[PDB]
Image: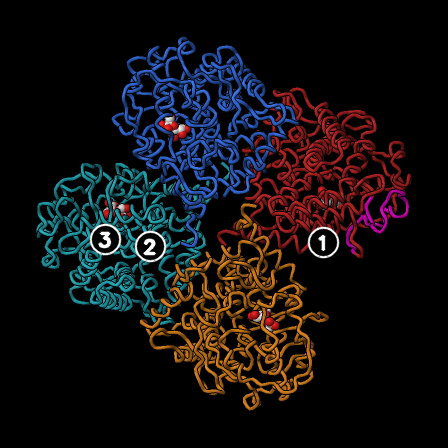
Chain colours: A cyan, B blue, C red, D orange
Amino acid sequence: PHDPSFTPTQLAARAAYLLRGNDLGTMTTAAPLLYPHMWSWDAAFVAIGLAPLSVERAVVELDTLLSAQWRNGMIPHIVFANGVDGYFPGPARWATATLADNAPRNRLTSGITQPPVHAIAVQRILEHARTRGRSTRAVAEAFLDRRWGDLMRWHRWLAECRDRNERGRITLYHGWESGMDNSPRWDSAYANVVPGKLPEYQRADNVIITDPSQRPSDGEYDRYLWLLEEMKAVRYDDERLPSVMSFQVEDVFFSAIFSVACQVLAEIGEDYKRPHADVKDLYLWAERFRAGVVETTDQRTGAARDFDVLAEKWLVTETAAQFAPLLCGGLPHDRERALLKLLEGPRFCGHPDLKYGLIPSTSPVSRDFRPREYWRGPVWPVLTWLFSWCFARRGWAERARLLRQEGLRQASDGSFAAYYEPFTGEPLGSMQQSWTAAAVLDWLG
Amino acid sequence: PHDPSFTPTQLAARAAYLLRGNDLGTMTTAAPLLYPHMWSWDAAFVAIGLAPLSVERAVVELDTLLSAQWRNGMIPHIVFANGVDGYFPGPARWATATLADNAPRNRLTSGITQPPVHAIAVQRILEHARTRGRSTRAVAEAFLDRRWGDLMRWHRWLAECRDRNERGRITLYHGWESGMDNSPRWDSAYANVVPGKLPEYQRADNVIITDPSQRPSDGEYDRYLWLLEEMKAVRYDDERLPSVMSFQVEDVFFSAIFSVACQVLAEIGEDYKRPHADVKDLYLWAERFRAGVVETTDQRTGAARDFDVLAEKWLVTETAAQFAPLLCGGLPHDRERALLKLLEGPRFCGHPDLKYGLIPSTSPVSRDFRPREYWRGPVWPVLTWLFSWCFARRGWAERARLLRQEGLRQASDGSFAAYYEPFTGEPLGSMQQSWTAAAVLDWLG
Amino acid sequence: PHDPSFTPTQLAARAAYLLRGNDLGTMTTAAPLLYPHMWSWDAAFVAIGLAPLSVERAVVELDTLLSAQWRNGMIPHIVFANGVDGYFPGPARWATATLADNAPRNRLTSGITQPPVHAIAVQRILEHARTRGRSTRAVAEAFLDRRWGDLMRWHRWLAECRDRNERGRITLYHGWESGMDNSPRWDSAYANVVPGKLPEYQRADNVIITDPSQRPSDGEYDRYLWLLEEMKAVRYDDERLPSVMSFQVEDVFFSAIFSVACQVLAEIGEDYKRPHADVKDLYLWAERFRAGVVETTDQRTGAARDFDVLAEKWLVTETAAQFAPLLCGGLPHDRERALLKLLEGPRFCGHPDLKYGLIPSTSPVSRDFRPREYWRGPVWPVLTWLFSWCFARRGWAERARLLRQEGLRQASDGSFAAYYEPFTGEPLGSMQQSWTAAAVLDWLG
Amino acid sequence: PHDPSFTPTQLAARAAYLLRGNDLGTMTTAAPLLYPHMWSWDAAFVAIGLAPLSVERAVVELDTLLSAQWRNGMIPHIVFANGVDGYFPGPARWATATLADNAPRNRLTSGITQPPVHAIAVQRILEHARTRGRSTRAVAEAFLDRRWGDLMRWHRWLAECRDRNERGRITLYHGWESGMDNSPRWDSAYANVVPGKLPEYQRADNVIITDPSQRPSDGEYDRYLWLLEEMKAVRYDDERLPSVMSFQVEDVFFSAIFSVACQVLAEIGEDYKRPHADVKDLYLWAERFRAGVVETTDQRTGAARDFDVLAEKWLVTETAAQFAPLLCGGLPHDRERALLKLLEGPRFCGHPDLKYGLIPSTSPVSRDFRPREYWRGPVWPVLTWLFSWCFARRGWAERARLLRQEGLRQASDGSFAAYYEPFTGEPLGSMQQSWTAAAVLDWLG
Ligand SMILES: O=C(O)[C@@H](CO)O[C@H]1O[C@H](CO)[C@@H](O)[C@H](O)[C@@H]1O
Ligand SMILES: O=C(O)[C@@H](CO)O[C@H]1O[C@H](CO)[C@@H](O)[C@H](O)[C@@H]1O
Ligand SMILES: O=C(O)[C@@H](CO)O[C@H]1O[C@H](CO)[C@@H](O)[C@H](O)[C@@H]1O
Ligand SMILES: O=C(O)[C@@H](CO)O[C@H]1O[C@H](CO)[C@@H](O)[C@H](O)[C@@H]1O
């Protein structure tokens, strides 16, 4: 009625109730019907949201994801729930269990990756555990003993297999790997993907989300699905993908995340007396990908650019990803002030028509902006959380506080949507998204 | 470490996480292992705790309980979960499905009842629903259309079958029906229960709670189980129980609760335009059981007494139940002040060694007091909740606030135990008790 | 910015900062410029707001007001600050120090009274004091020993000199005594006030509040000032006022407050062992005025009516005073339900255009409604507080909680205005009003 | 009662009430009786506590302090309230108005300085102002135009007159200038202060704080007062002090604060387009003093050391000043990790006997530790606040949050003491200390 919003305690309660409701036992679905399996970077956020409720169950979430890690170290972006249908492309379409030498045994997974936020969830689990006493500490530490090697293999796979030329940037072979499926970042790269004879399919995502303005188009799905055919034709062989993939881009946002994740994991390794050779490698990669992100940046504004490896051309777009250097650091002082000015000004957080002071996925003044269409404009709580946590780690305590405060105010409707209309605040996409509940739980403390 | 307690938002989150974790689908276990089925007055508290999370799921909890209501109106105190073991006495021991003409079809239940707090949960669901908008209101109101008749039948069964002589007090045939299994209230009545040839059994409750100081003794369980044999021998026939039961007491606390519940349900009936004949009956019963509670009271202190129907004697004990008149009203002004003085003084809430200003189940100065032993002394959050809600309804806003504040401070460890050691605050009994999570969720708002 | 509202801790801090800022030493001004003196019922609310900050200073506030008590027991409505100007009518206009034999020595005061909320403030001080331990309790208890007789003489003067016929209603001789200066309630009584040669004067209130729509008119002020001339002509003699005053009304809202105050004071008197003769008179008055209030009510709706003693007719208006019987109790059950329906429906709190679910001073559907004009429509936090506190005392916990929640939400801009535009929420009148800061402090706890 | 602690809203209210109560009009006293004047770094903290209440009044506090700035740029450590006595040494003892050519006109001040936390207060005022909209921003920005030059001259006088050899450390001539009057840090420098004929005097501090264990000794005060005699003999002339002062130490904690302050002011200067020459000097000073602090540190532990200029030796003590390098940065990675280990281990925050996880002024295991004796062991909320704010600025969000949480928990008794017994939590010294109320206000938000 007069105010549909919840008090902080009611909101924290409903967020926890949602997370437990999406729990299948050892994995949490990313959303009840739209995404009824475990997604890789959602799972890292889910573990962050579970850490204040049960360190034991947070550790189980990451254990389940890492039990699905490929033999070469890749963490796949989907871990399918056994017997669960209603999402396409499903395990039969991927065919990794039959085609991929490196796929895991006794887990069904996708054949592509997703951003490495996992070290950040590990840090949040350890910080919670240290406040809870000896038995909880022992649980977190036993997780580190058991999974430190797997986490190194994950980071080593990204550094060696997706940065073969030691450029300090991660190459993607599918826009889904960026986490930002239909971002304007990838449009010119996708315009050069030409599907051959693509085997028939029917979408399931728009059976659940039926408003066509909130999901990608059929044409885009045709190209997403064709990339799978190219990968399957070389049996997901790392050494053959550069020769056959019609889509090869360096993702500067993914790269900045990895730089931060490496630095975070190195600090964990020093704190918990892990092998010194591992710590040294992690710091080396943190600095390499820091330098690789800075190398992309606009000389006047500091804005970071993606790179089309096939066209050999910088990709200039006005999306939230151009703020990648703020997460990892490395810009000369003057260019970082200009970048912060871009972020806070009327092209992004300071745009006059925004309901909240939050980062829209695409600038509202760009021609590519669509207020409802997924990553082409809507405000995503997950991005708010990540920028706020990274800003606090840069020492920008008031900036991080302001993002948290506006994220909580947006989330106070209790819809736990994945993204929101930037001008009206209408929730969009699936309600009951686990990683939005998790961001709220982490923010509320 | 330095403070093991949780912030209000962390506590609300953990309470909601617990409640969803105990959800089997359409019923919530009272506790994970000790009480792995639905209990009647726990279920009413569970619905109160769910109301701020999901009015739809709160209504489902009460629907599931009422689908197990007996044909004569009795709400049984256990609704067993199909296929679930580990609690004794289980459905085979009760044998209501085969022996009891009035038992429900397609639910397994016990053969005794428990206090009628259900109307209070209905009120809390309606108050939540009215703050949430039209579709949520429609859910609550549709529950009333569907279940008003069942709620009347429940109240009518208590008024006509457990108060056959219109004394305005409820007769119990088992101490389990009071909710206070081993309370000192029932000791002299139980000393006159003599088991005949009692069929062999093994306890399950002390397999889970192994500290013998926190559960009833074998001798007590022998008498609890023998009462079942007396009931089974007359096939749970209402008309035969007065002739065969070795245990027949009027429970003044149960009676005060019923008086309040009748008044609450009458007000609901007027608000939602239910049949006027039903409303008039409810008000008639509210006043009858009010007068029946007052008739028991000590002339100097206002303390309410239970009555042994077989011995025809008043039962004088120093437990929390002697504060029954405060819940329902009816005492002359002067005797109610004396009763409040008893409650707040050094025999109860003002005892100098209590960790919290809360109501111990038995007075710490009584010879019957045992600080660990179930209802013989420990502080129960459920009683705190009930006294605080009833006090607020009497208009004693500061008294109700003080009980809430101390209940939250006791619960801030996040153990959600059913009862606590009164002097040390050590949690006792089962951890993860649903109705303690529910009281916390309701208090926190 | 995006959110001009303050957090609960920021709002409590600002309210306390305001209250200390309006403190002249032993008295607190009602507002810095518009009301730079001590007003009687404002000081009662100020003492309530001070009690969480300093029981000693809260008691000082009531000590200072009672030091200005007249010899017949009347608490005058203004205690003027020595040396302060800028308010009209000031002490020279009242001339009480010259004319009124009953006026106090070494205090300058007005010559009329205001509603008796003081006992309520005493209850709140005592409640706070009992949570703070022994030396704070001594302070509050020493105040009771010091001022019990004065409080008794205040109540006795109301019961005997302003209810000379034992009708259970308080007679007023000025609309200012109601606290609701320009209420539609008094329009037809004021229409029969015809001033003679009125000594010239210049208003000061509208030099500070310059928007003419927020204060009464010059014609209204000419009648206010003429009644002063009538009172001065009989030297404020009680026995002579009925013979000369052109304005004599029974104020049902003032009477309901008095009934409540008497009941509160009687209970205090019992708890602290005051003379029995006093407690008995206080209960007698509480009931007489409860009955006097109910005698005014409409048989169908329960709406309470004021009474014009000179015209000998019921004053039928659509203002918040209609709900007088909800504060003090006493209506038949059906009639009280009808009155709550009026309060919650579209003529008051349910009006669809209201920004908050709060009680407007005049019904938006009444022809008398003026959205900006003082007591002719605006929402006053002081009424919100008083209705909420009295509702909680009736046992209507949820109704009291809703008013408190909407009051805090309206207050959270930090203006601490005395009244707000009902549709837009715009603050009106003076900002920095002490009793609005007090209500916020008491609500926030 | 059972809980003498205050809720967060009650505590914010009481803190704000205290701060307004210590307001003399344009200055706030450090404490009502012990320190009834304006102290320099207290006023910086007071302005931080005022910023959530009134940006205008926060700016007044710094305006008043800067109006007492000496002509050479020095901010003196006391600005005396006109007409107030009860503190010794008072203005007659300092005699600055007579002797010091650089002393201000129409202000009475001391003749020594105190740490430069003022730029930090400026940042907090600006941060608050930017959340309050345009007219509040104008206030803060007009203050910057008014006082930027004065702030520059304050920093320039520190860099040029108290670091005459460009060593990047501040030289002090009195232990009072460190803010840590009786710290063990200065014990061996004070042992070489031998007073001559000292003019008689009577202490006032220990007439108010009478427990001798909470204040320095008479022998200590005789040395404090003798250094005044030395300064007065050269008429507080900067160029002459090195030739005559018996106490000359480089204060590494003061230096670390200055480095931070310079960096803060430089960033403010960039954001508000101050002269480039000024911003460049501020960054130069920030780095010089960062390097000067690191030059003092132990190679294994990172602990920072003070330096006795006269004795020409490092002062090795176990106090909170050792952690100077954590505030300003600059240590090698390994050495900073060792220093955090010292801070968190059993010699400081990890000591098993501490009631709160806070930084004691002197290590409990040091032979110099005295649990009640001022800066020789007690926990000071002002240090908690300053370490927490500086930790957040380093990016150590969780470490800053833990200090804030334990500080609020220690403060929640509402004493607002300046220091607390480290083992029992007993408040010590003066209650009603303004900068403890300020820290609480800033923490609570
Ligand atoms: O649309 C899809 O089918 C998936 C493909 O992975 O993308 C979304 O679904 C995932 C589950 O929420 C998210 O992690 C991604 O960021 C993205 O929003
Ligand atoms: O001990 C048992 O086996 C059951 C019998 O019903 O009693 C407890 O178990 C129930 C489940 O919590 C409670 O409702 C009762 O109040 C009581 O505490
Ligand atoms: O306008 C005035 O001159 C004074 C006269 O008493 O009235 C208001 O001012 C007083 C101080 O706020 C209040 O007690 C009253 O409610 C009233 O609204
Ligand atoms: O004891 C004294 O006479 C004064 C001298 O300056 O010192 C304290 O008093 C001042 C006011 O609290 C503080 O600024 C200092 O930290 C110090 O603790």
Please tell me whether residue C97 belongs to the stretch shown in magenta: yes
Q: Does the magenta stretch mainly form a helix, a strand or a loop?
A: loop
Do the residues under discs 2 and 3 have CB atoms within 8 angstroms? no
- Which residue is denoted by mark 2 in the rendering? A124
For label 3, the crowd category at 10 Å Cα-Cα, with few meaning under 14, some 14 to 19 and many 20 or more, is many
Q: Earlier in the sequence, mark 2 or mark 3?
A: 3
Vertical position of residue B3 compared to residue C122: above or below: below
Query: Which residue is more in the foreground, D198 or D274?
Result: D198
Q: Which amino acid type is marked by label 3?
A: Gln
Amino acid at circle 1 = Leu
Q: Nearer the viewer, residue C438 or D67?
A: C438
Q: Is residue A386 above or below residue D202?
A: above
Q: Which residues are magenta?
A: C84-110
Crowding at label 2, few (<14), some or many (≥20) Cα neighbours within 10 Å? many
**What element does badge 3 sit on?**
loop
Please name the amino acid that badge 2 sits on.
Arg
- The image quadrant of residue C183 is top right
Q: Are marks 2 and 3 on the same chain?
A: yes
Q: Which residue is mark 3?
A: A114
Give the x, y percent position of residue B409: 48, 44
The chain ID associated with circle 1 is C
Q: Nearer the viewer, residue A422 or C387?
A: C387
The residue carrying mark 3 has its beta carbon less than 8 Å from ligand 1: yes
What chain letter is assigned to the residue under label 2? Answer: A
**Disc 2 to disc 1, how far (Cα)?**
53 Å
Secondary element at tag 2: helix
Element assignment for label 1? loop
Ligand 2 sits in which quadrant? top left
Q: Which residue is mark 1?
A: C33
Per the model, the C-alpha gap separating discs 2 and 3 is 20 Å
> Vertical placement of A163 versus B164: above or below?
below
